[PDB]
Amino acid sequence: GRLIYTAGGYFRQSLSYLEAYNPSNGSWLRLADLQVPRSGLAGCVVGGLLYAVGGRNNSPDGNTDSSALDCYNPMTNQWSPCASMSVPRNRIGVGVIDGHIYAVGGSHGCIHHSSVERYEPERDEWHLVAPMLTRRIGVGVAVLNRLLYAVGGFDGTNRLNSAECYYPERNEWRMITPMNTIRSGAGVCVLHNCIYAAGGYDGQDQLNSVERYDVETETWTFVAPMRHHRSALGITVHQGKIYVLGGYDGHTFLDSVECYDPDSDTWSEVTRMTSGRSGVGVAVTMEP
Ligand SMILES: COc1cccc2nn[nH]c12
């Protein structure tokens, strides 16, 4: 696509913002607010449309975990509700395979889910698939070569270095090599042939480290760390570079956006969000 969209998030309370960053000229555009504020959601794009999945509305009126799926059309600048998931999923992870949205893990109150469900936009229906081997909230999800990966998180008792892969034609999850770092709330994405995990919280500190899993060699390798430690960051890929957005560094809700160039193994600051926030959903599609 052309723009990096950030939806929702948290600063003092859950947020409704939808804002779009254009890497080609540095500009930010404020677009139509989400109908319901939410943090801990995930974003993804299918068929040019932006989807906001899950989350939680932390507000003075109370706290409500979200089973919602909502769809933003850049052509109209309007959000439309879609079918809701089987369960609320705060701190969810999502990935897209073959035009279907997989919703992974997350929490509903004290319930930490291992369940996973798949949304078919052509039918506006969700269906449960095989659950993960581990309960995971704050889980990072990415897709490579039509396989789905769930990375890190929190199982209700422990933060996790483990990761697992879903094989759709077998409707089966299998563990993969664990990361070298415990990470909940990391940013997880794919670049070339590797699954990247950036940042997160290891139980003691917010992290700046970044490691990547080569699906051929089944090993994790550290790359250059981010300039800022951050948990509950948003992450996406644009033009072969990783962008990380916001998060919490143990002191401030960050407005920093950093960009990773894999050829030089360096991170640089490329813009600031209009306000600091964590727990955003992020995805890339065409300008509105
Ligand atoms: C303050 O302790 C925490 C709990 C859960 C997630 C977190 N991310 N950064 N700090 C965290």
Image: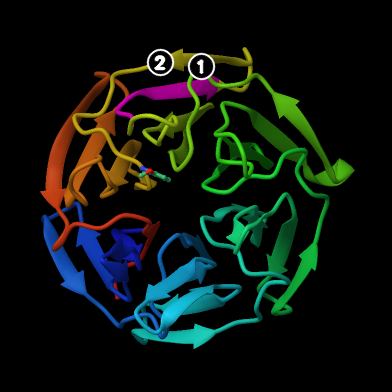
**Residue 282 placement (x, y as % from top left):** 38, 57
Left or right of 40 on screen, residue 219: right
The image's colouring method is: rainbow
Left or right of 6 on screen, residue 253: left
Q: Is residue 222 magenta?
A: no
**Residue 254 placement (x, y as % from top left):** 19, 49
**Residue 243 placement (x, y as % from top left):** 30, 43
Mark 1 vs 2, N-terminal side: 1
Q: Is residue 48 visible?
A: no
- Residue under label 1, please give it: 180
Quadrant placement of the N terminus: bottom left
Q: Residue at x 62, y 27 (%)?
A: 162
Q: Quadrant of residue 241?
A: top left
Disc 2 residue: CB within 8 Å of ligand 1: no
Left or right of 15 on screen, residue 227: left
Is 72 in front, or is 184?
Answer: 184
Question: Mark 1, mark 2: which one is toward the viewer?
Answer: 1
| Circles 1, 2 touching at the beta carbon (< 8 Å) | yes
Left or right of 23 on screen, residue 161: right
Q: Is residue 148 visible?
A: yes
Is 57 in front, or is 241?
Answer: 57
Q: Residue at x 26, y 78 (%)?
A: 31
Per the image, label 2 sits on a secondary structure element best described as strand
Q: Where ligand 1 lies, by quadrant? A: top left
Q: Which residues are magenta?
A: 207-213
- Residue under label 2, please give it: 222
**Residue 267 placement (x, y as % from top left):** 21, 28
